[PDB]
Length: 124
Ligand SMILES: O=c1ccn([C@@H]2O[C@H](CO)[C@@H](OP(=O)(O)O)[C@H]2O)c(=O)[nH]1
Image 1 (cartoon, rainbow, N blue to C red):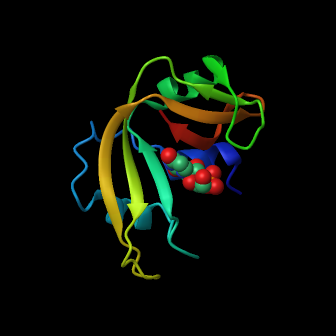
Image 2: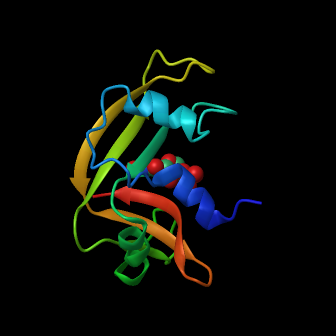
């Protein structure tokens, strides 16, 4: 009984740490958040800002989604994030990732009532 909003929080939110993600961060996080249960999710981004700040993006800059849909929004301010990218030698179930911190604008898709983030589209 996990909503799309809850799923977005599980896959993309990590407010706790003021971003100091070690080189082990993604290996631990991708596993702890169950993103390597059925397969090694190739790419996944974690946002370190507050839930309120990320939810607020749904009222910010409306931009086209990569899939052509029109319900994506870009944050006006840059946000602290951590990108997780599966390594080349990574082999399920032992999913391995490269951890890379960044400060960029995020683009999320929003749906529902309340209108909240349900998909992370990209960082720019
Ligand atoms: O910078 C990026 C690009 C893509 N993705 C994620 O990679 C998947 C394929 O695009 C998407 O996950 P989903 O299918 O569960 O919504 C998207 O959120 C990220 O996390 N960060």
